[PDB]
Amino acid sequence: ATLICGSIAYDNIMTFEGRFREHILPDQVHLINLSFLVPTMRREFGGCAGNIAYALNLLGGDARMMGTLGAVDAQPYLDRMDALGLSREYVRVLPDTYSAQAMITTDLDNNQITAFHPGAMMQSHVNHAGEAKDIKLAIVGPDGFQGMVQHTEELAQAGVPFIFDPGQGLPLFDGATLRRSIELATYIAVNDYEAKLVCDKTGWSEDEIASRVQALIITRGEHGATIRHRDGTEQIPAVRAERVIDPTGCGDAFRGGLLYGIEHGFDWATAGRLASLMGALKIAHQGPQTYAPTRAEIDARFETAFGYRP
Amino acid sequence: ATLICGSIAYDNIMTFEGRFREHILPDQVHLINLSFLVPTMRREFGGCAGNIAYALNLLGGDARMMGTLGAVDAQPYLDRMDALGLSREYVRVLPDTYSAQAMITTDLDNNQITAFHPGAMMQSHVNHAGEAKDIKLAIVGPDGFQGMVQHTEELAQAGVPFIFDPGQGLPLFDGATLRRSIELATYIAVNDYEAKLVCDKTGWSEDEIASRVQALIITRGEHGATIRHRDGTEQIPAVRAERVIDPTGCGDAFRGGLLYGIEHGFDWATAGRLASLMGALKIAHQGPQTYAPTRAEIDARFETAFGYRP
Ligand SMILES: Nc1ncnc2c1ncn2[C@@H]1O[C@H](COP(=O)(O)O)[C@@H](O)[C@H]1O
Ligand SMILES: Nc1ncnc2c1ncn2[C@@H]1O[C@H](COP(=O)(O)O)[C@@H](O)[C@H]1O
Ligand SMILES: Nc1ncnc2c1ncn2[C@@H]1O[C@H](COP(=O)(O)O)[C@@H](O)[C@H]1O
Ligand SMILES: Nc1ncnc2c1ncn2[C@@H]1O[C@H](COP(=O)(O)O)[C@@H](O)[C@H]1O
Ligand SMILES: [Mg+2]
Ligand SMILES: [Mg+2]
Ligand SMILES: [Mg+2]
């Protein structure tokens, strides 16, 4: 039983089939102008807690989402949760407010620029992580600020180890509130851009961050991930992608892997290789939760890549 | 009379209250992550022909829109065209189709990253600029590719001087078709990022392009603009904006200025100055056509900025 704290949201995703990096011109006053053709809209199921629970559930883990929806557009997400066998124990639905929505425009480098309507996520703190029953592991992901803070406080007071993924909630934090949460965290899992943002805001070095947690994990897209102890660092490979369609959700799939790895007491290598696999399988499909491998399929792909079953 | 060829669209603009240039980290695998709070939506009147005609009309010029709207949602745009006094004679409405709609993610530097669902714009070639009566000046702006090429061809054979502003539709062109259109154009106006993209694609230098046209106009956001014209070069100052809310549509406001000036026989310095003023006026509001200065105020602001009346 793994408590999954984070946004539950509707995503509207616009993926440039290319890399923003190729189209930056520093020398101009206009740094980048792009206009790319896209077909009909399709609203996706997303949010950080949503994505992480999905990935964990794909692996055959027990995933308890803790987060907030709004009653006006809740049902299609609640029904999906029901159809998938995801518990709504800590999924709170608030009468007469809208659920979070993310307008995400991105490229194949996962440079997500999101216009975010927090909606019901502004109330995330109505859930109390401490109250959760028989939790073995948790993750605290991007969410309402008061929610993120509270979740870290209650889980550390409960001695429930958690991964802390501030991700897209970093702007809500300051030096003092980011340091506090990182002090309460068992693991920190960020992408390399977020690590630098964290380094800046905390005024801490990576060395100083790694000293305070059990593991510092930094994902770097197609270049894999780093799993840092204070006594060692595993270099995690990227599983070469069948094809690259949409990286939106890759962070969250990877954390699906991590959470499974940790709760089963995998070695750090195997934990990260499994996380990295989830990352590679997602990127081949449009949206955070459009991939749907079977666990036998995940298992087969893992043994092909690495020569053993997880 | 002035023919304005280009898109008619509804704009959904997500302006970062900031500048992307400040959040880029090149030394990282992920160049930029952002996730910024937005108010709820507001479907704006937009599209390049829609924007240009609007600006010209505010100036009391005669603006004939040539574009294609979708019958499913064309009425609101058409009714407002009515309200504003904009002729609908070449605004062709395609039965059972959607109007073009843009999702524009931007910043205060006008770094537009746009996902564009063209719909009825894909049919823009149904309009034949050769058939437009009593036109003495034209502009061919971003539109469906067949439509853009056609206008360029048909205007040149009709002997209508025109500004070619290919802007967002550059990816549709190749070296040959772009060199063809510049050859047919009397004037070119683009932003500075576009100017370098045109150079790259045509293989022509900026000196070589200016040789083939009566004027090459290069806009530079807050830096103003340049007008290269055979027998001289003007460096148009920016009119310091009241406030900088949304630059989306600034290019198109500017082109309205230019088109009014050319038709009314201003010199390049004065026409570029009214161009600069129209963009300064627009930037003080959200969206491309929100701004509604009277001719009196345009007259007042011009003199305040420049010390005379054109
Ligand atoms: N400011 C935010 N707070 C919470 N969640 C967000 C925010 N911005 C985007 N998201 C969610 O972030 C998810 C993508 O994260 P990732 O899995 O790291 O690619 C999407 O499913 C969005 O719903
Ligand atoms: N282009 C890619 N190819 C293979 N795996 C990827 C790619 N992008 C992301 N991933 C996987 O997903 C993880 C998270 O991606 P990111 O959030 O973009 O750092 C990475 O560390 C990889 O394991
Ligand atoms: N690919 C495209 N084709 C035609 N028009 C576009 C495209 N992308 C954006 N636009 C329009 O361009 C306008 C903004 O251009 P600008 O006036 O140069 O800032 C908006 O009103 C959009 O509707
Ligand atoms: N921040 C700004 N302040 C004042 N004027 C501006 C600003 N941005 C754009 N303009 C005007 O609008 C024109 C077109 O802008 P752009 O399409 O960004 O090159 C510029 O040449 C300026 O004259
Ligand atoms: Mg992430
Ligand atoms: Mg010529
Ligand atoms: Mg433009």
Image (tube, coloured by chain):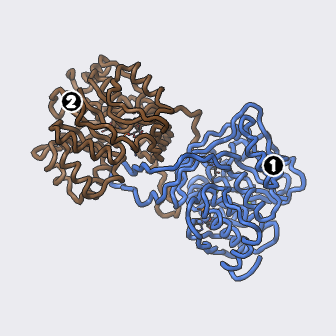
Chain colours: A brown, B blue
Residue A82, placed above or below residue A108: above
> In whole angstroms, how far apart are the C-alphas of marks 1 and 2?
71 Å
- Specify the subunit that label 2 lies on: A
Q: Quadrant of ligand 2?
A: top left
Instruction: Determine which residue is flagged by label 1.
Output: B154
The x and y percentages for residue B135 are 86, 56
Q: Is residue A87 visible?
A: yes
The x and y percentages for residue A54 are 35, 27
Instruction: Determine which residue is flagged by label 2.
Output: A135
Q: The disc labelled 2 sits on which kind of residue? A: Ile
The x and y percentages for residue A22 are 46, 50
Residue at point 16%, 53% (across, down): A207
Q: Residue furthest front?
A: A95
Residue at point 24%, 57% (across, down): A176
Residue B297, placed above or below residue A141: below
Q: In the rendered view, does B185 fall on the left or right side of A168?
A: right
- Specify the subunit that label 1 lies on: B
Query: In the image shown, does B244 or B234 lie closer to the viewer?
Result: B244
State whether label 1 is within 8 Å of ligand 6.
no
